[PDB]
Amino acid sequence: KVFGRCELAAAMKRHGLDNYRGYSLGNWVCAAKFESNFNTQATNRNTDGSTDYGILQINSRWWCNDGRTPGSRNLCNIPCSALLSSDITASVNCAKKIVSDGNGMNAWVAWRNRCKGTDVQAWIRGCRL
Ligand SMILES: [Cl-]
Ligand SMILES: [Cl-]
Ligand SMILES: [Cl-]
Image (cartoon, rainbow, N blue to C red; front, side):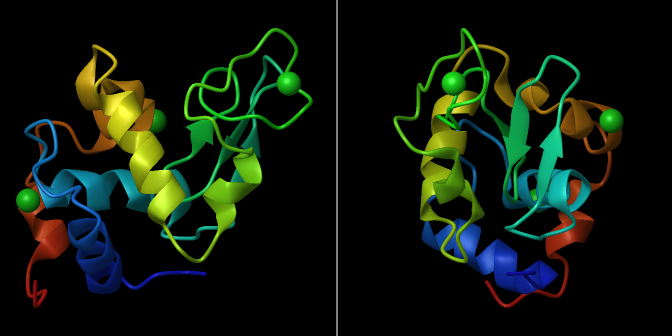
């Protein structure tokens, strides 16, 4: 599913991501924009052989199981395929664990490089939330 901007903001809010660990909704929408362009089915293969999955490009080295990332963990206790669903529940619940792991949203390098320090509220501007 490719979400609309406000549609995704609303779904993220419904799932308790808004201001989670102090990160406003615009931060999460911005991260999703640059990680996946709001496409739940986004996948990307990393140089180390791991893969990133879903709207927030969650990585199989630590967070989910895909059966083909040697030496990896599955800390969200989910198949990586669950992160591709039209229902963002699994991605959100896993993101909550990731952002609580110590480095906040810096875990998403694209958030650090493209969202951090910017006017992230622009991502939810106009949205009925
Ligand atoms: Cl915001
Ligand atoms: Cl594996
Ligand atoms: Cl980047």
